[PDB]
Image (cartoon, grey):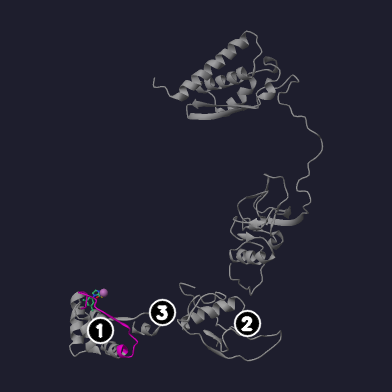
Amino acid sequence: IIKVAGEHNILPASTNPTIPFTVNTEAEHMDMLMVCHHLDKSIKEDVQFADSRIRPQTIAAEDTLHDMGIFSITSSDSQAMGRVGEVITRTWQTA
Amino acid sequence: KTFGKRLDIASGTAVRFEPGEEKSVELIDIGGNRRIFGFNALVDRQADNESKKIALHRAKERGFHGTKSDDNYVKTIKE
Amino acid sequence: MKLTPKELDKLMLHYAGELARKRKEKGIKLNYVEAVALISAHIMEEARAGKKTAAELMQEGRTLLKPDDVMDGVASMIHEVGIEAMFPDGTKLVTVHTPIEANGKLVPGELFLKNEDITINEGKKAVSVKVKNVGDRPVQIGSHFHFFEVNRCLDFDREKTFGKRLDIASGTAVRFEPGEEKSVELIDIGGNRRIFGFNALVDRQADNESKKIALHRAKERGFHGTKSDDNYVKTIKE
Ligand SMILES: Cc1cc(C)cc(-n2ccnc2SCC(=O)NO)c1
Ligand code: NI
């Protein structure tokens, strides 16, 4: 989905729980994904679904794309995988 | 090669072609938001590589000379 | 009794017929109203009796009145008499056709016509086209239908019929049985020649530019006998 941020007619935004990229980010997001979808580690299809969702490669690319001016808006996604009191703080942490 | 382009001449001037005449012209990219509406209704949307295929298919069906779009064209949901 | 309004109206009709029958027994020549009432009342009683069909009553109604029983002019005024009556299988309509023959010369509302013919569609030159029905169901075409847009199972040279209609009397029609082949006469549509509807093959001004679009549309929808060339060039509004 990240490839649409290069297009002319798209105004692209990121939400704050993935910025900035830290050493606790991937494990936290994986355990959030397992709870909300009620997945089980003993099923090979839930594991295949989860490993196609989180993707630390694109998460790592997101900060650099913010620094290049390719992403243009930051936001919260409040109480739905995001923190409503931390948009400004996480923007300046990323900078 | 001319999709999304205009003549590189002074603004308000023009280039004339007599019958049978052949010459070369210079073309540069259209600026701004590059939203092309009107002119023959071959685009009527944002100019990009996705809209170029639709425009080439439309130009071939209406008989514009020199347009090359391949056979077995795949339609989209909004053309 | 629980009488309905229909029952009350039919009771009145029965006694009108009875008065007509009494006047006929006294030797009085019946007028228009009396003759109609007498025939209607007789049919209703015969249907109540239950021993005859409606088709037999349609013929029995023609023997009730001789030509000498009515006044001069009555027989030319009565073309048919209709009456609904309840049989053992329910209510049916019985129509009696030409119940009385005429014997005098008085014709009320008589027409005196000239003997010259009427020329319709003057100044319109006709062309002739051969048409064949290759379908399995009958087709009938009216006088002012746009003949280019008729049923796709009719096979004919459709290019020659663009902007044309049948050259017949207004309100009449031509019938094609399955497998039937015959020729028809066609003339140009008049007025502003703006054709809207009929199969939505034109929906605009009829001219040579609109004929190419109509032929392409007719070929794509499978109308028989339409010939439009390959490598068709689209316009901006089709
Ligand atoms: C990664 C994640 C985190 C959370 C809190 C919920 C979901 N989750 C569950 C079902 N559907 C979704 S994705 C919708 C969303 O979180 N914002 O639109 C996924
Ligand atoms: Ni959300």
Indicate which label's residue lies in the foreground, 3 or 1.
3
Closer to us: A63 or B63: A63
* Amino acid bearing label 2: His
Image-quarter location of ligand 2: bottom left
**Location of residue A56 by image quarter:** bottom left
Residue C201 rendering spot, x and y as whole percentages: 61, 61
The x, y position of residue B57, in whole percent, is 55, 78
To which residue does mark 1 refer? Answer: A54
Q: Residue at x 62, y 63 (%)?
A: C218
Magenta highlight on residue C168: no
Q: Is C93 in front, or is A68?
A: A68
Looking at the rendered image, the quarter that the C terminus of chain C falls into is bottom right
Task: Determine the chain carrying the residue at label 3.
Answer: A
Q: Residue at x 62, y 65 (%)?
A: C219
Query: Is label 2 in a helix, a strand or a loop?
Result: loop
Q: Residue furthest top?
A: C26
**How far apart are the two marked residues, 2 and 1, measured between alpha carbons?**
50 Å
The quadrant of the rendering that contains the N terminus of chain C is top left
Residue C45 location (% of width, % of height): 52, 19
Q: Are marks 3 and 1 on the same chain?
A: yes
Is residue B69 found left or right of C183 in the rendered image?
A: left
Chain letter for the residue marked with disc 2 in the picture: B
Which range is magenta? A65-82
Of the two numbered discs 2 and 3 in the rendering, the one whose residue sits closer to the viewer: 3
Disc 1 crowd, CA 10 A, few/some/many (<14, 14-19, 20+) = some
